[PDB]
Image (cartoon, rainbow, N blue to C red; front, side):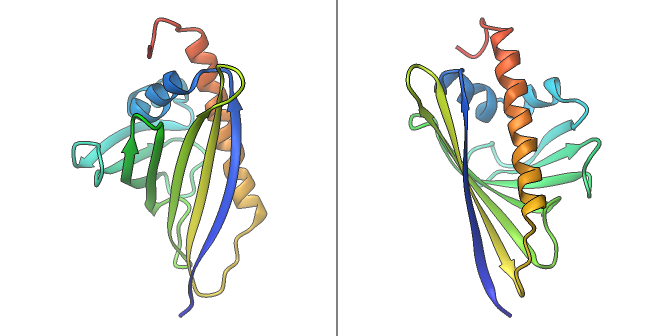
Length: 162
């Protein structure tokens, strides 16, 4: 049975400077996200580990989830370089034919003072590979919205994540 890896890059941009964002979005996601999108994210909970490399998180969704949750395994976190890698491993985007999805995200400092969020997504496939543009671009939008909500919030809370 054919094993393979579908790979998809995209970027977003943001006014928020890289480090604030990293603290908010990566480092306190568990807390900050449910606060600002309770429609779409009920809860977030660490099943195992500190929360560094090797941790397993269950994230629990509200409306607009096929399965109503995911689990993530954190592969790495680099606070100094502002990068993050993990793997979706059980739940929402997966199936018999998509064993796993890997994300790696690099925040980079744009011109001038702002940020560029670079994400690379890696679909570990089994068997024939059908991966619909929809399911993928639908995903882009979800994340794009979510980052927009973070910008907005953080701009309304400048005493935070400094």
